[PDB]
Image: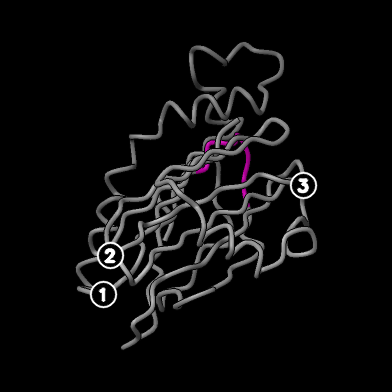
C-alpha cells in the first residue's frame, strides 16, 4: 500500500536546517523528500519482490512510485491498455516522502503483454502521466514513459490510442519529463517481469 512518513511542514520544522525559517517552501519539502528517498525504499522493493513471487512467470510490471514533489499527489486516472491491475486497490493519495507499490500484469493465459498507466495530480494543478509497456514478444524491449502536463491533459489533449502509440514506439528503459516546477522520471528493467520505478520531484 503506502510506505514512508509524509514529509510536510511539521516534519521540516523539527529539522535543524529549517526550524527557524520564516516560510518553509514546497521546494524545501521536496528537497528533503528527495534526500529521504532511500529510507523506506527497501520496504517498497520488498513489496515488489512479494508481488513478483506471488505472480510468478508471465509478463508484468512491479511498479514503485516515490513522491518527492513537496506536496501530496492524488491518483486521477488508471488505465489498462493491455492486461489488468492486481487485485489490491491502488492508493488514492501519496504524501510527499511516501511510496506506493502495485503490480500490473498481462491478461491471464494470453500471449499479450502488460501496458497501462496511472495519472497523478499535484496541488499546483499538474497531472503526471506514468505509463509502462512490457511486451510479450521479446524481439522488443520493456518501455516506460512519463509526461508532466497541465491538469486535465489526458485524455482530451492525449487520447488513449495516442498514449499507447507512444508506449509502443518508445525506445528507452528510462524516461524524463518536466513541466512548471515539477519533474518526473521513470525507469524499467528490460525483462518479462520487470521492476519499474517512477520518481516525481521539484
In terms of depth relative to the viewer, which is nearer, 31 or 154? 154
Give the labeled residue for mark 2: 192
Q: Secondary structure at mark 1?
A: loop
Q: Quadrant of residue 130?
A: bottom right
Magenta highlight range: 67-73
Left or right relative to 27: residue 89 = left
Cβ atoms at labels 1 and 2 below 8 Å apart: yes
What residue do we see at 63% from left, 39% from top? 71
Give the labeled residue for mark 3: 150
Counting from the top left corner in percent of width and height, residue 64 is at: 40, 52
Residue 58: assigned label: 1
The tag earlier along the polypeptide, 2 or 3, is 3
Q: Quadrant of the N terminus?
A: bottom left
> Which residue in the rendered view is the most extreme toward the front?
139
In terms of depth relative to the viewer, which is nearer, 17 or 49? 49
What residue do we see at 74% from left, 64% from top? 155
The tag earlier along the polypeptide, 1 or 3, is 1
- What crowding class fits label 1: few (fewer than 14 Cα within 10 Å), some (14-19), or many (20 or more)? some
Left or right relative to 166: residue 62 = left
Counting from the top left corner in percent of width and height, residue 138 is at: 29, 65
- What crowding class fits label 2: few (fewer than 14 Cα within 10 Å), some (14-19), or many (20 or more)? many
Q: Is 159 rendered above or below residue 58?
A: above
Cβ atoms at labels 1 and 3 below 8 Å apart: no
Left or right relative to 119: residue 176 = left
Q: Quadrant of residue 114?
A: bottom left
Asked whether 191 falls inside the magenta stretch, the response is: no
Amino acid at each position: 500500500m503506502l510506505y514512508g512518513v509524509e514529509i510536510d511542514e511539521q516534519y521540516l520544522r523539527v529539522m535543524e536546517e529549517y526550524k527557524d525559517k520564516e516560510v518553509i517552501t514546497q521546494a524545501d519539502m521536496a528537497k528533503v523528500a528527495l534526500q529521504r528517498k532511500n529510507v523506506y525504499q527497501d520496504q517498497a522493493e520488498k513489496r515488489q519482490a512479494e508481488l513478483k513471487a506471488e505472480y510468478g512467470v508471465g509478463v508484468c510490471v512491479l511498479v514503485r512510485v516515490y513522491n518527492a514533489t513537496g506536496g501530496p499527489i492524488t491518483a486521477k486516472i488508471e488505465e489498462s491498455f493491455r492486461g489488468h491491475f492486481g487485485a489490491h486497490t491502488r492508493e488514492k493519495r501519496i504524501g510527499n516522502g511516501q511510496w506506493t507499490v502495485f503490480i500490473h500484469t498481462k491478461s491471464a493465459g494470453a500471449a499479450v503483454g502488460s501496458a497501462g498507466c496511472i495519472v497523478y495530480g499535484t496541488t499546483d494543478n499538474l497531472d503526471i502521466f506514468s505509463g509502462w509497456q512490457n511486451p510479450w514478444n521479446r524481439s522488443w524491449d520493456s518501455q516506460v514513459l512519463v509526461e508532466v502536463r497541465q491538469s486535465g491533459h489526458w485524455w482530451k489533449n492525449g487520447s488513449k490510442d495516442y498514449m499507447l502509440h507512444l508506449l509502443d514506439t518508445h525506445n528507452g528503459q528510462n524516461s524524463d519529463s518536466s513541466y512548471g516546477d515539477v519533474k518526473a522520471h521513470g525507469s524499467t528493467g528490460n525483462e518479462t517481469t520487470a521492476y519499474v520505478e517512477y520518481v516525481y520531484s521539484r
